Image (cartoon, rainbow over all chains, first blue to last red; front, side, top):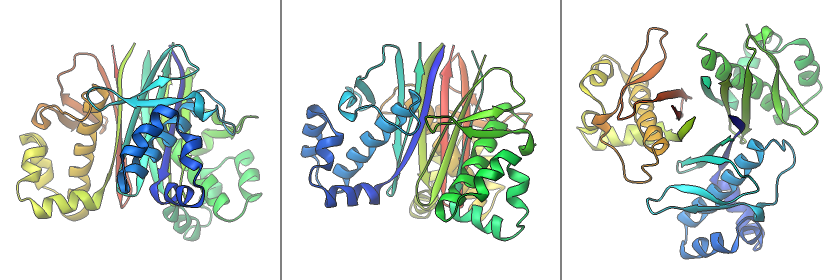
Length: 116
Length: 111
Length: 116
């Protein structure tokens, strides 16, 4: 049984500005764990990681049906498994979370299906 | 069980040009209620609304494997889009997202 | 029951750039059947056909959870059915495969949901 579906696309450029404008931006979007990875990356890759996590958390909040509003981003965590696939390690959901992220040089995309 | 799946991506500029060419475009793509909402918006936001509804209907049509006036996408109190009308009696899981340049729509039909 | 979900987005210019730089790119990515339709196409359309198939194969691999590692691209095939929709004619999966592809003049995206 499907209980939610949400997608999201981000332009990397705007995540770039957000980071540049507010030094606390990434700190507010990412969890401690996520932030540790964020710090091990540098130029483009660091922004791609951040943009991907933002995209995933947004897609998840929409899958939960919050339309305008969003769940706390600190209540959501996305890590990579042994194989490099991203998944939700933390989430206010108990069912199965099917997540997928893809990206180009300028955009990042995310899709979430919730199953009960 | 899933009985259908469709997605769509649209270039916002492409939706304008359309609106620019045959101006009767929007009236043909949107329903009355949808139009009231459209004509009450302006700037980038108005084109996004149109692109968003187009994209939503395209994805749904592809999910069905198949009239836009027969489809209507509104927004609930939470701001989330959803099909208020559609030639389908099961659950329609819809999601839309957009940037300054593009819009994407994903649809999953379930029974 | 959903057992896998994957998406992918591709900038057409990247695909165009890969064909230009590598003469046998298409041959490595497309099966004999796919290669037929491909060669019968020209310009942008040809690139878009190639990009979509690559996008679809990429989305399927993620849906399988393959992560960064990947399956044979020759082990996957995407043709068009009698209703004119793209589908996997060959895939190491025995359940239902839901595929959808879409593109602009600049990008192409694919979404795959695995069910059984």
